[PDB]
Image (spheres, coloured by chain):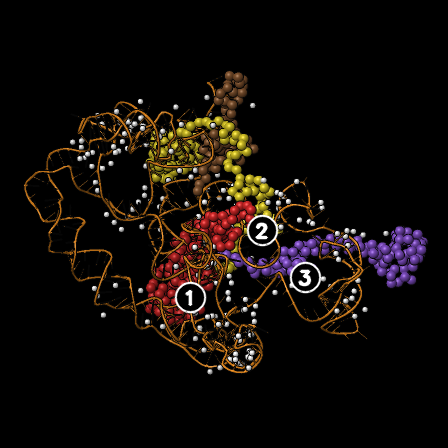
Chain colours: A brown, B red, C purple, D yellow, E orange
Amino acid sequence: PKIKTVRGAAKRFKKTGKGGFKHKHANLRHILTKKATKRKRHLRPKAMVSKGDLGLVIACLPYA
Amino acid sequence: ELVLKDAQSALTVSETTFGRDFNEALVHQVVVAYAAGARQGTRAQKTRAEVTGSGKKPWRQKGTGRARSGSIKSPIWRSGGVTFAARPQDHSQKVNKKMYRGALKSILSELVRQDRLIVVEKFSVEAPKTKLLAQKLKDMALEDVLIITGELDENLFLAARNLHKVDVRDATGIDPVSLIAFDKVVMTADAVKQVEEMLA
Amino acid sequence: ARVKRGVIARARHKKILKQAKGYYGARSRVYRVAFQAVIKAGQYAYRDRRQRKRQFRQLWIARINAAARQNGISYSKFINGLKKASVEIDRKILADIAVFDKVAFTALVEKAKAA
Amino acid sequence: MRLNTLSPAEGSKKAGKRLGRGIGSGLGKTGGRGHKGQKSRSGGGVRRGFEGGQMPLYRRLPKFGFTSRKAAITAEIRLSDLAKVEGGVVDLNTLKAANIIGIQIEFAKVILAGEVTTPVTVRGLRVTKGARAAIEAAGGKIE
RNA sequence: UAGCGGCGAGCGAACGGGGAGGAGCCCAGAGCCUGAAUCAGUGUGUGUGUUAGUGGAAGCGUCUGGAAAGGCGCGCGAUACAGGGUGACAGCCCCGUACACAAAAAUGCACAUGCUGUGAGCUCGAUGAGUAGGGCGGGACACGUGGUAUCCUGUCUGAAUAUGGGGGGACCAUCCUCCAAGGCUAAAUACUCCUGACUGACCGAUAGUGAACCAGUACCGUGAGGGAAAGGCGAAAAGAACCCCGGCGAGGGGAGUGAAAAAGAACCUGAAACCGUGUACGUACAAGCAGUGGGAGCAUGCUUAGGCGUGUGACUGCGUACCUUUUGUAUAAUGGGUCAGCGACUUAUAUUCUGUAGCAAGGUUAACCGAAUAGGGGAGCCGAAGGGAAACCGAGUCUUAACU
Ligand SMILES: [K+]
Ligand SMILES: [K+]
Ligand SMILES: [Mg+2]
Ligand SMILES: [Mg+2]
Ligand SMILES: [Mg+2]
Ligand SMILES: [Mg+2]
Ligand SMILES: [Mg+2]
Ligand SMILES: [Mg+2]
Ligand SMILES: [Mg+2]
Ligand SMILES: [Mg+2]
Ligand SMILES: [Mg+2]
Ligand SMILES: [Mg+2]
Ligand SMILES: [Mg+2]
Ligand SMILES: [Mg+2]
Ligand SMILES: [Mg+2]
Ligand SMILES: [Mg+2]
Ligand SMILES: [Mg+2]
Ligand SMILES: [Mg+2]
Ligand SMILES: [Mg+2]
Ligand SMILES: [Mg+2]
Ligand SMILES: [Mg+2]
Ligand SMILES: [Mg+2]
Ligand SMILES: [Mg+2]
Ligand SMILES: [Mg+2]
Ligand SMILES: [Mg+2]
Ligand SMILES: [Mg+2]
Ligand SMILES: [Mg+2]
Ligand SMILES: [Mg+2]
Ligand SMILES: [Mg+2]
Ligand SMILES: [Mg+2]
Ligand SMILES: [Mg+2]
Ligand SMILES: [Mg+2]
Ligand SMILES: [Mg+2]
Ligand SMILES: [Mg+2]
Ligand SMILES: [Mg+2]
Ligand SMILES: [Mg+2]
Ligand SMILES: [Mg+2]
Ligand SMILES: [Mg+2]
Ligand SMILES: [Mg+2]
Ligand SMILES: [Mg+2]
Ligand SMILES: [Mg+2]
Ligand SMILES: [Mg+2]
Ligand SMILES: [Mg+2]
Ligand SMILES: [Mg+2]
Ligand SMILES: [Mg+2]
Ligand SMILES: [Mg+2]
Ligand SMILES: [Mg+2]
Ligand SMILES: [Mg+2]
Ligand SMILES: [Mg+2]
Ligand SMILES: [Mg+2]
Ligand SMILES: [Mg+2]
Ligand SMILES: [Mg+2]
Ligand SMILES: [Mg+2]
Ligand SMILES: [Mg+2]
Ligand SMILES: [Mg+2]
Ligand SMILES: [Mg+2]
Ligand SMILES: [Mg+2]
Ligand SMILES: [Mg+2]
Ligand SMILES: [Mg+2]
Ligand SMILES: [Mg+2]
Ligand SMILES: [Mg+2]
Ligand SMILES: [Mg+2]
Ligand SMILES: [Mg+2]
Ligand SMILES: [Mg+2]
Ligand SMILES: [Mg+2]
Ligand SMILES: [Mg+2]
Ligand SMILES: [Mg+2]
Ligand SMILES: [Mg+2]
Ligand SMILES: [Mg+2]
Ligand SMILES: [Mg+2]
Ligand SMILES: [Mg+2]
Ligand SMILES: [Mg+2]
Ligand SMILES: [Mg+2]
Ligand SMILES: [Mg+2]
Ligand SMILES: [Mg+2]
Ligand SMILES: [Mg+2]
Ligand SMILES: [Mg+2]
Ligand SMILES: [Mg+2]
Ligand SMILES: [Mg+2]
Ligand SMILES: [Mg+2]
Ligand SMILES: [Mg+2]
Ligand SMILES: [Mg+2]
Ligand SMILES: [Mg+2]
Ligand SMILES: [Mg+2]
Ligand SMILES: [Mg+2]
Ligand SMILES: [Mg+2]
Ligand SMILES: [Mg+2]
Ligand SMILES: [Mg+2]
Ligand SMILES: [Mg+2]
Ligand SMILES: [Mg+2]
Ligand SMILES: [Mg+2]
Ligand SMILES: [Mg+2]
Ligand SMILES: [Mg+2]
Ligand SMILES: [Mg+2]
Ligand SMILES: [Mg+2]
Ligand SMILES: [Mg+2]
Ligand SMILES: [Mg+2]
Ligand SMILES: [Mg+2]
Ligand SMILES: [Mg+2]
Ligand SMILES: [Mg+2]
Ligand SMILES: [Mg+2]
Ligand SMILES: [Mg+2]
Ligand SMILES: [Mg+2]
Ligand SMILES: [Mg+2]
Ligand SMILES: [Mg+2]
Ligand SMILES: [Mg+2]
Ligand SMILES: [Mg+2]
Ligand SMILES: [Mg+2]
Ligand SMILES: [Mg+2]
Ligand SMILES: [Mg+2]
Ligand SMILES: [Mg+2]
Ligand SMILES: [Mg+2]
Ligand SMILES: [Mg+2]
Ligand SMILES: [Mg+2]
Ligand SMILES: [Mg+2]
Ligand SMILES: [Mg+2]
Ligand SMILES: [Mg+2]
Ligand SMILES: [Mg+2]
Ligand SMILES: [Mg+2]
Ligand SMILES: [Mg+2]
Ligand SMILES: [Mg+2]
Ligand SMILES: [Mg+2]
Ligand SMILES: [Mg+2]
Ligand SMILES: [Mg+2]
Ligand SMILES: [Mg+2]
Ligand SMILES: [Mg+2]
Ligand SMILES: [Mg+2]
Ligand SMILES: [Mg+2]
Ligand SMILES: [Mg+2]
Ligand SMILES: [Mg+2]
Ligand SMILES: [Mg+2]
Ligand SMILES: [Mg+2]
Ligand SMILES: [Mg+2]
Ligand SMILES: [Mg+2]
Ligand SMILES: [Mg+2]
Ligand SMILES: [Mg+2]
Ligand SMILES: [Mg+2]
Ligand SMILES: [Mg+2]
Ligand SMILES: [Mg+2]
Ligand SMILES: [Mg+2]
Ligand SMILES: [Mg+2]
Ligand SMILES: [Mg+2]
Ligand SMILES: [Mg+2]
Ligand SMILES: [Mg+2]
Ligand SMILES: [Mg+2]
Ligand SMILES: [Mg+2]
Ligand SMILES: [Mg+2]
Ligand SMILES: [Mg+2]
Ligand SMILES: [Mg+2]
Ligand SMILES: [Mg+2]
Ligand SMILES: [Mg+2]
Ligand SMILES: [Mg+2]
Ligand SMILES: [Mg+2]
Ligand SMILES: [Mg+2]
Ligand SMILES: [Mg+2]
Ligand SMILES: [Mg+2]
Ligand SMILES: [Mg+2]
Ligand SMILES: [Mg+2]
Ligand SMILES: [Mg+2]
Ligand SMILES: [Mg+2]
Ligand SMILES: [Mg+2]
Ligand SMILES: [Mg+2]
Ligand SMILES: [Mg+2]
Ligand SMILES: [Mg+2]
Ligand SMILES: [Mg+2]
Ligand SMILES: [Mg+2]
Ligand SMILES: [Mg+2]
Ligand SMILES: [Mg+2]
Ligand SMILES: [Mg+2]
Ligand SMILES: [Mg+2]
Ligand SMILES: [Mg+2]
Ligand SMILES: [Mg+2]
Ligand SMILES: [Mg+2]
Ligand SMILES: [Mg+2]
Ligand SMILES: [Mg+2]
Ligand SMILES: [Mg+2]
């Protein structure tokens, strides 16, 4: 049978041109008023997955 | 060109299709794949599941001095098991059109270099009789041959069944293993023309 | 393609049991026991190629040390006597000479007495 | 060449790992899978994205976005693969019969992929600013 | 993939496209006219299968040998060299085979077809009510009540019925499309107790069925049920008349048969553990993984006037099995009485990487038809473009009012 993609992983990562994956930063859902705006600003844009935890992502979604 | 043995006519052929370097790996792959495609692969053993018997424990886990057993059907036990039982399976491995054509083009060109390929004009026996075909191959110094023909004639095809060293394929139905197998290939001028257009 | 393995196994066991020929009891008869014996034999054999070169040196030294003390010099002073006279002759031969040609050997002890 | 004299290219075939076949084999007794633990066990090994019970990366991170229904049915026509249809008319249905874009694609776009020669009148397709310069430089009109 | 999902584990479409295969109808009924299409009894000649079968080509001499089919020499058939048997391996000895044939009788199909027995075409109409829908509770849909369409119904209700109604994924309005609440229908599709032929990089007696053998047997269990072991003399029984020892025994030795009787029915080959008998050497003051270095003697085959090669091994240096598991094992931790046989990284499909081969801005086909692994088939897939949540823009683009 075909490999099933880990769907939850498909909904949190997106494949970039070179091969890596963009993902949204954690700590930006609730409890925002106590956070400084400089954090919240820096957490807003999408960010790349580190080389340590890349193999875990590549495994759980083999298609794209 | 392909010189004939009863005419000496300059039969012009494509320099590619009948004049390439011998790509050995390609030909080996195509002939191995062809030979694989011949396998029917009809077999099975029976796993510990499929063997007849019960799922009873022969003896209880403890207390007995025996080595803890769980089934009479286990592969380490005699009579019933075979750990990785076989199953019927399609061995027919895939071969790229271009690789197959390229391999034929290759092996069909080495018959010119090695002088196995005896290209001829009209090749047909009188009546459906092996006796005649046998007598006419004696003139040509041929014994083991693959007589490839354009118009497949009953007179010829029916006079080469019983001859083990003579096979009569149609120009459409040439094969990688067959061209290599037979000591000579007696090809008809029409068959060369068909094979030329087929391989391209 | 099922592979029976009785022809090969037998040949493999029979090979080792041929190397264990001469050993006591099960060590010659019984593959499972022989195979250990044949390995340990090889281990000891490998070891004792090293020990052979040690034992013989001792043996020779003890012959030379005996043969020199009959002439009145100890092995320790004798070898220094030979080395200070730049004599290149080894223990193997000195020990051979000591036994066979004592009248010759005596000359080396004089040659050593010079130094 | 004979049926026997054939041989493969050097490097093509590589035998294959055969575990549990003596000392000399190298791998043999614990078929290259160490001593004990879940990974040594037959049918062992943890599932994908399992970090020992720590909350996995694909769950500690937040989920974002929505999949567009429209993007599925739009195409990105490379300018090089444009003069391969019917002289110089590329509506959409003509471009589809050339097998350049899929059947269920109603919107399409011609981007600056490079290389045009013949004059192509592009009618209906949305055209890029870089491609509009090229297509017109070659001679072709738009709309 | 879109979705679903303690948005976890996992579950997972549809539209659309390519193929196989194709076919449609009948009632809720009046008309002029009607046996016409149709499927319907059954006969009925037919075809051409099935159940018995018939014919079916061409070899000879020498050489080993128990025996020739084998070696060598000369031939001959071949629409037949598939295969099996015959005293060893047979195109021509036999049985078959290709091929040509064959039914008194019983049947399976495929066209005429007399017909108990059956209606087209018309006009006109009608066009499925406790039903659709709803509330309540459940289940089915990829879809877990979720914004949840659609389907089914236990329960309580309840329309309009063709200017009518259902559906287009909450819902509404326009557009579009269909006609529910009555039915029927071959093919492509699934399967093989069983029958016939043929085929295997399937097994060859611990394998292959549990079962090559009188096996679902012996045997075990109150019973349901479980469930073995066990193949082979030789070409031919020519299966050992007779004589001898013994109890008219078993068993043996002769004789005879045979190529062979260490092929004598406990029968091809006949391994190992294990047990003997005979030789050579060692061994009754010597301590221990039993060997290994060194090494005398004795016994030996050879040669030769050389020494070796073996067998043994007095004395002597060193030396605590193997596997496992462990920081670490002679360990008094595990496992093994021995031998022989079997006994554990496979398979399929996806995916990524490496080698390799093809072709390269291209590469490649799937099911499918075809009959021969070719050739079609490019439906599709992957690549040549990315950024953005997305619209969208695009060698850029997102960010932001804009960004050096
Ligand atoms: K025997
Ligand atoms: K000791
Ligand atoms: Mg990319
Ligand atoms: Mg920072
Ligand atoms: Mg994909
Ligand atoms: Mg090569
Ligand atoms: Mg079962
Ligand atoms: Mg039970
Ligand atoms: Mg015990
Ligand atoms: Mg079995
Ligand atoms: Mg494979
Ligand atoms: Mg076999
Ligand atoms: Mg073997
Ligand atoms: Mg000894
Ligand atoms: Mg022995
Ligand atoms: Mg030393
Ligand atoms: Mg040293
Ligand atoms: Mg010195
Ligand atoms: Mg290599
Ligand atoms: Mg393999
Ligand atoms: Mg290795
Ligand atoms: Mg290792
Ligand atoms: Mg290796
Ligand atoms: Mg081991
Ligand atoms: Mg272990
Ligand atoms: Mg453990
Ligand atoms: Mg481990
Ligand atoms: Mg399991
Ligand atoms: Mg398991
Ligand atoms: Mg695993
Ligand atoms: Mg297409
Ligand atoms: Mg621009
Ligand atoms: Mg939770
Ligand atoms: Mg399911
Ligand atoms: Mg599943
Ligand atoms: Mg369409
Ligand atoms: Mg089509
Ligand atoms: Mg379709
Ligand atoms: Mg079709
Ligand atoms: Mg068909
Ligand atoms: Mg059809
Ligand atoms: Mg069709
Ligand atoms: Mg039809
Ligand atoms: Mg119609
Ligand atoms: Mg109809
Ligand atoms: Mg009604
Ligand atoms: Mg007939
Ligand atoms: Mg007959
Ligand atoms: Mg005959
Ligand atoms: Mg004679
Ligand atoms: Mg005679
Ligand atoms: Mg003679
Ligand atoms: Mg004779
Ligand atoms: Mg005789
Ligand atoms: Mg004869
Ligand atoms: Mg001979
Ligand atoms: Mg002749
Ligand atoms: Mg023959
Ligand atoms: Mg014989
Ligand atoms: Mg022969
Ligand atoms: Mg003959
Ligand atoms: Mg035969
Ligand atoms: Mg012959
Ligand atoms: Mg016929
Ligand atoms: Mg009849
Ligand atoms: Mg008759
Ligand atoms: Mg009849
Ligand atoms: Mg109706
Ligand atoms: Mg009604
Ligand atoms: Mg409804
Ligand atoms: Mg309802
Ligand atoms: Mg509604
Ligand atoms: Mg509804
Ligand atoms: Mg409702
Ligand atoms: Mg209510
Ligand atoms: Mg409700
Ligand atoms: Mg409801
Ligand atoms: Mg519910
Ligand atoms: Mg459900
Ligand atoms: Mg939701
Ligand atoms: Mg909501
Ligand atoms: Mg609705
Ligand atoms: Mg109506
Ligand atoms: Mg109307
Ligand atoms: Mg109307
Ligand atoms: Mg209305
Ligand atoms: Mg309406
Ligand atoms: Mg609809
Ligand atoms: Mg609907
Ligand atoms: Mg509506
Ligand atoms: Mg809608
Ligand atoms: Mg929807
Ligand atoms: Mg829909
Ligand atoms: Mg409306
Ligand atoms: Mg209706
Ligand atoms: Mg109507
Ligand atoms: Mg309804
Ligand atoms: Mg209906
Ligand atoms: Mg209903
Ligand atoms: Mg109903
Ligand atoms: Mg209906
Ligand atoms: Mg019917
Ligand atoms: Mg039918
Ligand atoms: Mg066949
Ligand atoms: Mg075969
Ligand atoms: Mg087989
Ligand atoms: Mg066999
Ligand atoms: Mg058996
Ligand atoms: Mg046997
Ligand atoms: Mg047996
Ligand atoms: Mg059984
Ligand atoms: Mg009983
Ligand atoms: Mg037997
Ligand atoms: Mg018999
Ligand atoms: Mg026999
Ligand atoms: Mg007798
Ligand atoms: Mg008497
Ligand atoms: Mg008597
Ligand atoms: Mg008596
Ligand atoms: Mg008596
Ligand atoms: Mg008597
Ligand atoms: Mg008597
Ligand atoms: Mg007797
Ligand atoms: Mg006798
Ligand atoms: Mg006799
Ligand atoms: Mg005789
Ligand atoms: Mg004999
Ligand atoms: Mg006897
Ligand atoms: Mg005799
Ligand atoms: Mg014998
Ligand atoms: Mg008897
Ligand atoms: Mg016996
Ligand atoms: Mg016996
Ligand atoms: Mg027997
Ligand atoms: Mg025999
Ligand atoms: Mg026997
Ligand atoms: Mg015996
Ligand atoms: Mg023995
Ligand atoms: Mg003696
Ligand atoms: Mg003695
Ligand atoms: Mg003695
Ligand atoms: Mg003594
Ligand atoms: Mg003594
Ligand atoms: Mg003792
Ligand atoms: Mg001691
Ligand atoms: Mg000792
Ligand atoms: Mg002596
Ligand atoms: Mg002597
Ligand atoms: Mg010796
Ligand atoms: Mg020690
Ligand atoms: Mg010691
Ligand atoms: Mg352990
Ligand atoms: Mg360990
Ligand atoms: Mg342990
Ligand atoms: Mg411990
Ligand atoms: Mg111990
Ligand atoms: Mg220790
Ligand atoms: Mg112990
Ligand atoms: Mg202790
Ligand atoms: Mg102890
Ligand atoms: Mg213990
Ligand atoms: Mg333990
Ligand atoms: Mg152990
Ligand atoms: Mg024990
Ligand atoms: Mg594996
Ligand atoms: Mg792939
Ligand atoms: Mg790559
Ligand atoms: Mg290139
Ligand atoms: Mg192409
Ligand atoms: Mg088919
Ligand atoms: Mg088509
Ligand atoms: Mg085409
Ligand atoms: Mg096409
Ligand atoms: Mg790529
Ligand atoms: Mg921009
Ligand atoms: Mg801007």
Mark 2 Cα-neighbour bin, 10 Å: few <14, some 14–19, many ≥20: few
Q: Nearer the viewer, mark 3 or mark 2?
A: 3
* Disc 3: host chain: C
Along the line of sight, the residue nearer the viewer: E7 or D76? E7
Asked if disc 3 is less than 8 Å from ligand 15, the answer is: yes
Which residue in the protein does label 3 denote? C21
Nearest the eye: B110 or E62: E62
The residue carrying pointer 3 sits among few (fewer than 14), some (14 to 19) or many (20 or more) residues within 10 Å by Cα, namely few
Name the residue that disc number 1 marks: B164
Subunit of label 2: D
Residue E311: x %, y % from top left: 71, 65
Q: Is residue D20 shown left or right of residue E329? A: left
Position of residue E359 in the picture relative to residue E283 (left or right): left
Q: Residue at x 92, y 58 (%)?
A: C70
Are the residues flagged by discs 2 and 1 in contact, CB closer than 8 Å?
no
Q: Quadrant of the N terminus of chain B?
A: bottom left
Q: Nearer the viewer, residue D44 or E228?
A: E228
Which amino acid type is marked by label 1?
His
Q: Is mark 1 within 8 Å of ligand 58?
A: no
Q: Residue furthest top?
A: A33
Q: Position of residue C51 (x, y in %)?
A: 77, 53
